Image (cartoon, rainbow over all chains, first blue to last red; front, side, top):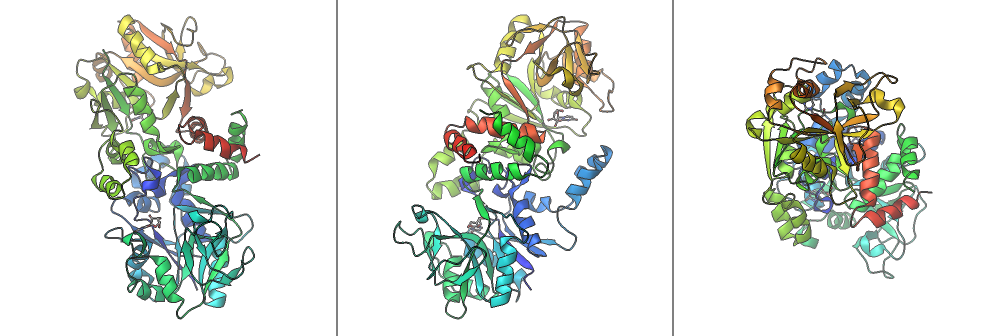
Length: 290
Length: 290
Ligand SMILES: O=c1ccn([C@@H]2O[C@H](CO)[C@@H](O)[C@H]2O)c(=O)[nH]1
Ligand SMILES: O=c1ccn([C@@H]2O[C@H](CO)[C@@H](O)[C@H]2O)c(=O)[nH]1
């Protein structure tokens, strides 16, 4: 039922300089692979079959990462690294396609989603903001649950995360009557950007994971330039409120913002430790520090 | 006076896959910046003025990193973010030049250095393998001490460090009568590549920093192949021994192989704990795991 995801990757990422001066922020090493691999894997495991990169002319390396590399593959055969060759050959399953479209100028998350209008078609679709990483624990990730909730209700889904009461002015927080249980959705009635401490309508932050109906593309074509003179996804979802129910899905797992330098380092530590091959020896490198 | 360093960066480096799949192994992010910045900083802080990259068709992103990026810089001006702008424009001082030459085919380290012949001319020169990072704690870095010593002695220098007896198996090892002290050089008879664990002439590994005379280039033209990697540098250094004193310089610093997954994870930890801004907040994140 939900088979397409739009990853908007066209932004230059001024927040993680100089690391992203000359390679995309999305290709920042996290333990042993680029950040984007963790987001694409997340999508794939939630049953996504078509990855739609809305990208920029400097971001070839993202596209090259999900494609074959002749010179790389033949030097791996020449060195008999057959296991590695099989790992870099099958980064993504056979049935998963990676499509690419250009965002002409950088005019907001809303405008980036709109650039995928022609590939989304009449299909309903997920959005995953790739600067955010999502870590699970049990089987079936937060995006899987949210998608099957969109399928159940036919209500737009907006992934949210409880944050401490003293911090809500850093986040977009949703207006909900009550807060749902982890793994569950509630009707929401708007999102407020960076509300002042003591005046926010919930502790539930917008994360950067959406499931939206195609209808939203028509709504983005009729939303005026908002905050930062940029055309805004939150403003098109406000408009969707006029005809459709919109729910906040509260995640069971934990996020990392590989857009800040400190959220990046947090992610390396948490992914490092959990690494199926390096985790133990990484923990050991930690201990030996002091 | 040693002004020129050769950085052989032409090899694909299949040991830090998949990080290095679609970006150069040299651009892999260490804390907040590509690994190669640490190596170019090492050279410049030790009086280098011409950085000679011996490079490959797939590594523009390295050249770009020490160049200016028009679209990114104006994006930063428009957004009035001038402290970031300063961190991406003054990456090396005005007086330091970064030069490119192509290694046509990957025929070994010696062939890389020989590709730099036309640029180095009649001048003496440093060689830096950027896969290895070298961290100081004195205020004079090991490359500086080793150049300072080439200048007096007029003896070629090979940076070396002591390894556990059971691992001499893994490393280039120098033939020395005796171990110099941390910070000094002894005469050396040559290098044994991966000596059998019992039968090595010392515990002192070749680290990947050299200071060599111009005439090594003629020598490199008249060395045959070695380990099916046409020209080998150590063969040329042996050929040098039949004319001049060659010395082994033992380092006071510490090393990290950013090609080995654990060596890279160790550089992230150590370099992060000592970052101006993030060190204290990073130290903080590490404690919050136990
Ligand atoms: O105009 C654009 C195009 C893309 N993105 C992407 O959306 C996320 C932040 O909103 C990041 O992944 C960024 O690269 C934007 O934000 N704005
Ligand atoms: O043919 C070769 C062999 C090695 N190297 C470089 O030498 C260093 C150590 O072998 C690495 O950074 C590798 O890229 C080259 O540039 N070309």
